[PDB]
Image 1 (cartoon, rainbow over the protein chains, first blue to last red):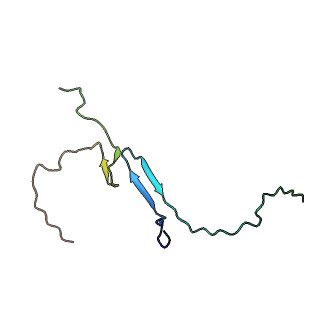
Image 2 (image 1 turned 180 degrees about the vertical axis):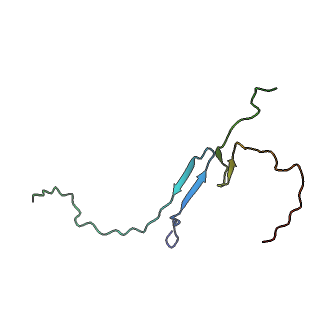
Image 3 (image 1 turned 90 degrees about the vertical axis):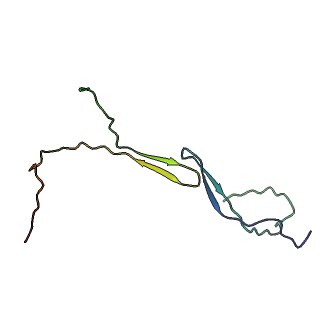
Length: 50
Length: 50
């Protein structure tokens, strides 16, 4: 299953007009996210005093 | 038949929205007109040289 896209890119905005001036707006957004390894594989309780 | 109005006054503007963003606009206008006696009861051929 590798070597094949699994989605579509779309960042458009569509307006649909119904009667009585109501309007359905459809906002579409796509972004490319970059993820890094976690600093630590642990949960940390951290205190912060300035 | 005298002493009774024969019309309605209306100077509004209405917008009707159909699908696909088409719009029907209905412009309504009323005015009170003043009419004076004709200067002459005749048809006149008039020349104008400046």
